[PDB]
Amino acid sequence: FTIAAKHAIAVEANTGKILYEKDATQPVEIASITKLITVYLVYEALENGSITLSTPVDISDYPYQLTTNSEASNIPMEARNYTVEELLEATLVSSANSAAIALAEKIAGSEKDFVDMMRAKLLEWGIQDATVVNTTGLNNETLGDNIYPGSKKDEENKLSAYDVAIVARNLIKKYPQVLEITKKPSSTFAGMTITSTNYMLEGMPAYRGGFDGLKTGTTDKAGESFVGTTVEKGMRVITVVLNADHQDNNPYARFTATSSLMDYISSTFTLRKIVQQGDAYQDSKAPVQDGKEDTVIAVAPEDIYLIERVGNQSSQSVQFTPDSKAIPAPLEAGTVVGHLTYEDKDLIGQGYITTERPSFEMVADKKIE
Image (cartoon, rainbow, N blue to C red):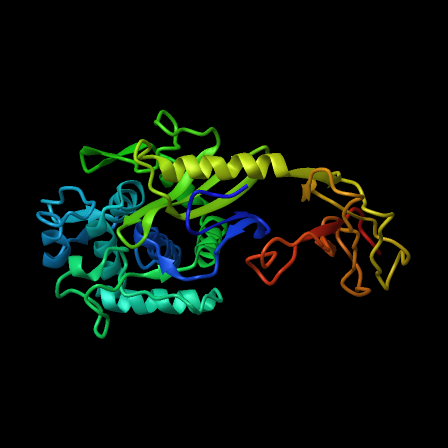
């Protein structure tokens, strides 16, 4: 299998395990996919409390004018003051650039400061090959004089599909709420109706059962790009397709390509349940040094699944409970007492988009002393 896109990568959301890749490390233009990094700082400000969903946000000259004549996906904002939630919805659903900019100025005072924030955030995540000059994903030539100091006039943000995967993963894992927005095939923006650019959602042309994200992006340099997330066959997959080959008879090539990528993933990988909730994966105990002494049976207290290729000579060694060494009492039933780690030997690409390999907590199913 090969994808009809210049660059792409697919990962299982939870573990960040790589399922498919094609030139996933070369930084390239990502257009509006940029708004994901943007939206992460917004939720982080909502969480910190500095802003709230109903907080009124002014819309300055720069973002406001950008909407009267800038063939930049936007929506009327003649009231120049909208809710954080309203802009958030406008940003993720319609890719409105003035929505993005507005939120940025609200959070950092200026798009520039906001960019420094997104540059810092990326470095936190271990992404050190990114190029961020704006919060929208547009090309600077579209921003005239409102470009980052030092940036070139035709510069564009750049991230690798690998990098994007990380971003998408961190966002979904830390702020699952975002899905309640990207999910909507249409919403309301202070009265008028906005339409999603994601055509794989409910009631849309390129619908594919399970989808509910994440962000499209199109630019001459970025091509037809789309970050999509979905739950297929019980597994959450994050998809990044960024530069779908342009097909003349299919405006939805980026989604077709994504749908194509998922047919591969679902027929190639599956989630085999290894441990049942309440049970123990190898009469598996963890030390306590005060009461009973021998055992706590450390047990799964949710069902544990692992990604597995289908067909593979005998299978995986996720045998492994370590404890965390022999601990004091009393030990309450339910407390974490060890971890089951999957020693994955079927690494695709760099294997994982995280330096951590999957480990699931094993709980104590009895009290001691």
